[PDB]
Structures are given as structure tokens and as C-alpha cells.
Image (cartoon, rainbow, N blue to C red; front, side, top):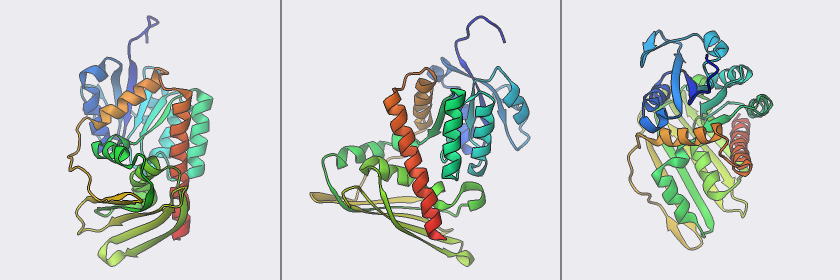
Length: 292
């Protein structure tokens, strides 16, 4: 520490699986290096030294005053605990969705963040996807009669990554962002343990009663895929441009987090995002209750 004003925010990355490794790689990007600098990283594995910084203990990350920001990239089941501890320690926090696997817990963290005067940011890169922007432009001025969004992928351990409504909350986020706040009508969950198969089907309604079906399907034989079928009073939409993953999509999310750090996001925008985030976590929580 030194009292001469500094140019950047010091960052600690907590958990270094695919997401944490991408955040570390992204910290090496030039323009992102104008505002941030990696201080250390925390991991359940013995990595020791990455990008020239030493691995540090959680205790050490929490106590260090050189660290202004924590990127929580651990398994989802630990997100809540890590966010709580870092906000308690006075760090701004960026966390990959879902921020928690509990609505009431998320409420507590938002309150803690406000009390500590820290930024709490839940990353949702799905809203930065090129095909999502396409969809947003296409549904504009149209009225949804009925639609479905299905995502198929491989099995996911619920103990570590959450119940499917939480682990797949990015698909629900798409629907809410595209069509507004949704009414939960019903939910069912089919599971065939012998086949490692799971299918969650959720019926939702837009405010004007357009029907939406959200399906999360997981099985060892499923190709990772998204299926969109939106029927409007004026035409239908079943194809979205075929786009590959964008290596810089997390940097786009980081740009938003940095604007929040610099106090460059309006109170209006901050409130609308939190309201959407909490609406989705509340739906996921209730969906889980309905699936029993």
C-alpha cells in the first residue's frame, strides 16, 4: 500500500475452472489492463503461481487491502458464501450467475452490498450474445402468442451447480429480458436416474398472457443445443443466426462491471437490473418448489 492515488483496481479471482481461467486470461487484455490488475487468486486446487502472481488463501484474500475486487468463479453452490465473505471484507464483487441458489439469500446479499457501499454484479453474458441482440430486435413491436425455448446439454451435478431452474437461469433470463416479467403457471421435472436423464418443463405467461414453455433437458446423449420457436400474432420465429462462442464476451461483461466500479451506471439502470435479477431468482426458487 502507498498513499499516492492509484490508477487501477486490484482483483482477486476466486475459483479457477473454465470461468476463472477466462477471467484471468481477460485480465491480460490491454484496454482492460488500463483499469484493473490481478493481485492473486484463490483455488481449492494447488496451482501455486499463475500469470506471475502467487495463489493465496481465502483468509489472505479477505484481509488484503491491496485487493479492491473479487471475481467469484467457484462452483455455484459456494457462490453465496464467498460473496457474503468478500462483501463483509469490503470488496466489490463480480460473480458468475447464479449468484445464489436461494432467493432469500440473494436478498440478504443485495442488502449487504448496499450497506457496505460495494458493487455486487451478477454476470449474465447470455444477454450479450449476438443472437440475443438479434432476438431483441426481432420481437420489437410484435406480440407473443406462444413460444418455447429449450436447452439440451449433458448432465450437471445438482449438488454443485444447482437445481436446473438455477443452473439454466440464463435461458429464463433471455425470456424475461425479451418478453418482460413473467407469471409462473406450472412446472414439472422428470428424472430417469438409470439413464442419467432430466427434463424440466416450465409454463410461464407474459403479462399479456402469451404462453411460454421453458424446457431444460439434460442427458449423456444430448448434443448441446438451443431451440427457439416464437409465434407472434404477426408471424413466427424459429431460426436465429448461427453464431459461434465469442472469446471476448466476458470482457464485455467486465466493461459493465468497471462502469459500475467508476459509478457510471445510472440508479435507474442499476435498479432495473437488480429487479430483473431478483425476479428470475424468485421464479427459479418457486419453480424448484413446484417440482418437489
